[PDB]
Amino acid sequence: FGLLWYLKELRKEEFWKFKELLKQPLEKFELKPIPWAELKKASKEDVAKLLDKHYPGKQAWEVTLNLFLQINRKDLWTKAQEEMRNKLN
Image 1 (cartoon, rainbow, N blue to C red):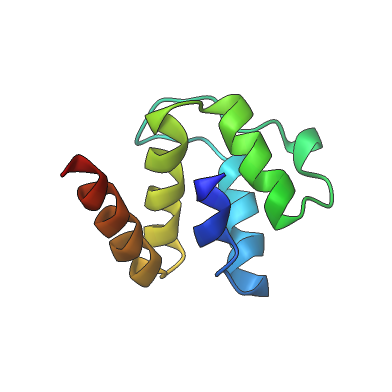
Image 2: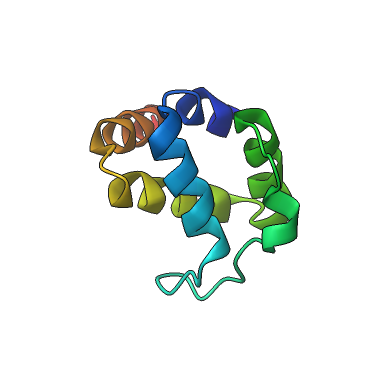
């Protein structure tokens, strides 16, 4: 779960916002939000698994990166893009 490598960097309040945003309408991608019942006491590892269950493929990364921007972690956005660009070489 390469997603978890970045998710682990969220501090407590940023992670709470991240989970709340996952349950709300995802208007930029017209995807279905994660049903709220599934995020009851979800740890960082659990969220990484839910992202891969619900938004497999590039979708999970698209969602996660967009949420990073909404919770003011553009540092993590930039790091994730850098990894993805390095994979294209």
